[PDB]
Image (cartoon, coloured by chain):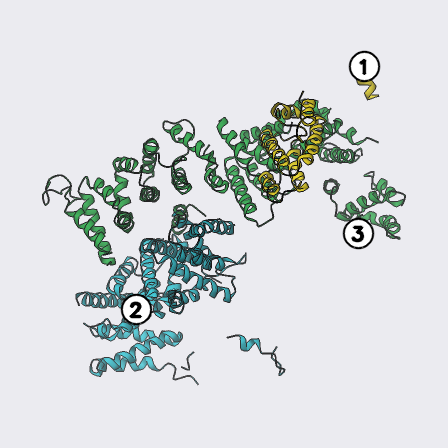
Amino acid sequence: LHRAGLLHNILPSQSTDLHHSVGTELLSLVYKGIASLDLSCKQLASGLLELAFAFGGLCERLVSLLLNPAVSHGEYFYSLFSETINTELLKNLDLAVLELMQSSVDNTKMVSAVLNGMLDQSFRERANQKHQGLKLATTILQHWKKCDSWWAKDSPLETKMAVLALLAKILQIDSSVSFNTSHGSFPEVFTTYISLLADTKLDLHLKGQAVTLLPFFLEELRRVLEQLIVAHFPMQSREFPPGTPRFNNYVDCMKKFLDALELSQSPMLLELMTEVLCREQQHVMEELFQSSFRRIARRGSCVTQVGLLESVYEMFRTRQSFVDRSLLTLLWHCSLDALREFFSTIVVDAIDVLKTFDTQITKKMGYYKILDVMYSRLPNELTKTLIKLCYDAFTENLERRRLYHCAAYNCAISVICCVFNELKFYQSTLSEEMSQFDFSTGVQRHECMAPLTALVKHMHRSLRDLPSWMKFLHGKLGNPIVPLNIRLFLAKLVINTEEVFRPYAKHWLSPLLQLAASENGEGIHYMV
Amino acid sequence: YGLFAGPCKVINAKDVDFMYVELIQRCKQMFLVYQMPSFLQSVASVLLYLDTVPEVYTPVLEHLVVMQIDSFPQYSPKMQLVCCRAIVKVFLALAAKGPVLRNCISTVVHQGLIRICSKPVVLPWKVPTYKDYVDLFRHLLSSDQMMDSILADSLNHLLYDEFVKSVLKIVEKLDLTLEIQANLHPAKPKDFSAFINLVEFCREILPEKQAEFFEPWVYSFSYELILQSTRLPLISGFYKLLSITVRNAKKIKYFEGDPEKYSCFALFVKFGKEVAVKMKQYKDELLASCLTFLLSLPHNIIELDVRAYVPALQMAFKLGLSYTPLAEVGLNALEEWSIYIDRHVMQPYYKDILPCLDGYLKTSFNKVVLKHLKKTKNLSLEE
Amino acid sequence: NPAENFRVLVKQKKASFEEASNQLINHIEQFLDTNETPYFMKSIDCIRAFREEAIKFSEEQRFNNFLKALQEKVEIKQLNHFWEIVVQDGITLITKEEASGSSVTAEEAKKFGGDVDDLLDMI
């Protein structure tokens, strides 16, 4: 009959549109069950619930009933049939929303419970749309300041994290395209959000697991970022023993930040995380550092990648470790189109700086380490000259100086690929529901010569006696007067490749033999 | 500390939950070894002791507990027992408060079976398995031997009821779609695999327990399952599930043809006749389910139109000749009915029965040295 | 972060605690290229706290020499974030404090080819 659009031909308005016959029985039965139950009476009470929903105005009565403090019993009645309550209240635009938004100044538990029921139900409401959830989110965004008992030092930490969880559910429900910057009621809740970030009373682990919603986003951002992260890691994380509680909190918060930034790819966060990691080696789990860089390099727009790379590069100007630990991952992995843009953007930016003093040397390492990798794809007008400016750099006849020599030589090895390509180099239903429930809980031997061998293989691809300097190196390592470290370098390199010069091994046996003769640091017998 | 918190609930009670709070971080830290049962039993103890808990942990624990099921494979059996006992303890601790009891158990068993059916079926962090948990499962329902010890300082039937409600919401939740592009072309075969996982894991834990616990569902449950059967009356799972159901019903002797009783019997006879006449178009792994259901009915309902049940039974033996369990169960049903139903009504088709009984009649390291053999530690048609 | 740790250490076993000395030395020293000026603020603050605790129990002359030597150390630290900040915020204590006199006297004492190319071609 209700689907036929009639409810008063059989039950006209008793005193109001509320035909309280349904609600009286509902409350009496739902209370008397404790002072008895059945699946039969469960579905029958559900039926009575949609009978009440057929009548109008009962929603305020339900709001009152769930506030029953009999000991609790109102929240108990809600818990018994939260599903039908969600179903009805979804139709309720904001009336009971305001009811709770006012009555919740004291009520804390059941109000949050029913709010999350609203959230998860409208989340389940997705077959047609979720715009009902969006309108509900906007309404509660406006409603936010009409109940203030939470979200300040007027409430305990449990209360604060309760609203943190509720707003997290909202954000993972709502469209971040709006209310991420200034959008009507956005600042109203956003200043609140910032203030709650500043709450030092909460554990930093809880603070991080709250701020994990950061991909939905400005000086306030960065400044709260530093003022929070400073209070976490003095200089070192592994100074705290692995497995100790605060160390575990550190690893949890850092991984949360890493994944959140990997999703958001916000530049200042990149600077902060690089710098905090660019303090000590492998104490900020640099493997996930570089691997998340590997993801984000293929993600995002090319212009975004270029801007982020320029941000970190400018931040670069130990100082060297900053670029060293970080950039190469992006450079070796970011989109090739973005590489064109970024390099073209920094052609003369690097030309000039290409030509105490230790800082100069560190910058020059970085420049060689970025030019060599940028060369690796494809061959402006000035591009002609800069090549030479690299080679001379190695040709110099304190260990940082040898590192510099290696830097220049590796850069030349790179750039010699396409130029001097000739010889003479001049040395589901179930899945979706499972995810919906996950949503409801909200929780789910030294190496410096590798490029040298690579170039050897490349020239083998492009191509006994050769002015490939295997004559020169044959004479070099044939004499034993060559220093032991140099012989080690040459031997370790030539180990990786000998098939290239098979019709020259008929001579190669002679040096190695006298090298094998009474050979004599990282363990002689290994290489022997 | 977990066994100590109760005494600590006396002096410095407000410390107990305090340390309890940090333990949550630990298991969150444990999220991402096999020390889970330690956590489970410790939290079980403290929650038995604790009476005030921040509710923010209620979903987390729901996520946490299911994790150990997730981690249940690759366990050693001993700490499998340890963790199952810890599960019993956590259930008993949470059973103190009825609301949280019912909601948490519902959601956790639901998510658990979700992940269970998520494990794919075979066709011709180590790799886990799905058949293990049923052993776990039998200990879940055979858990008096631990709830007694915990009550020192019914409930399995409560577990049974929760499980029945869970599987009800499962079977009503998932619905299957297919195409034919006689012919079949599933459109969500992953859901097919999940469904058959559900069937293969339940049709053995259901009958081993007592249908007396299942009794509050006998008319209702099967009905919807029959309803589900009526949705796609070409799925073997319906036949197996209802076959287990009717085994349980004859175990509890529900057939006395109550209005619910007579409705049950009427639906039984009508649907059995319908499937016994539509078996013509059903083949192996489907016709097998059909016949196994048809024999699984008791005498009382099938007294009406025994004749229609004869030919499939005939088939059930000649195909039972090729598949021994089918003939075995058909023979058990036949001897049952002969014991209950009089010979006179069975007399006319005896000349029919005997021809299909000709089957099963035409047929005909480790050395002497003491090593406390591991083979000893490792522990048809003639019947 | 180890600031409170060494505070409770020096007020719990009452020693100079060269471990605390190295903790504060590390807490200060790692400010060279990474501009942690807020961490530098917390650093100078825990320096004041440790100076007070040192004058308190037994480490009067201990942190006297410690703070003095670190004062000339930051003086020779030719940085862009250097003893300028220390002096402008350590207007209270930057040097030794035993009782008075020489202590406040110390406070007052501090608180207030290519080469040829460069030198001649462009001078």
Q: Say which colour chain B has.
A: cyan
Q: CA distance from mark 2 to mark 1?
A: 104 Å
Where's residue A394, x and y in %? 78, 32
**Would you name the residue on which mark 3 appears?**
A523
**Would you name the residue on which mark 1 appears?**
C121
Q: Nearer the viewer, residue A477 or A159?
A: A159
Q: CA distance from mark 3 to mark 2?
A: 73 Å
Give the image quarter of residue B46.
Answer: bottom left
Where's residue A240, x and y in %? 60, 45
Q: Nearer the viewer, residue B248 or B156?
A: B156
**Would you name the residue on which mark 2 appears?**
B211
In the rendered view, tell whether residue A128 sits above or below residue B92.
Answer: above
In the rendered view, tell whether residue A300 sits above or below residue A350.
Answer: below
Q: Secondary structure at mark 1?
A: helix
Q: Say which colour chain A has.
A: green
Q: What amino acid type should be assigned to the residue bearing mark 2?
A: Ala
Q: Which chain is yellow?
A: C
Disc number placed over residue A160 in the picture, else none: none
Observer able to see residue B282: no
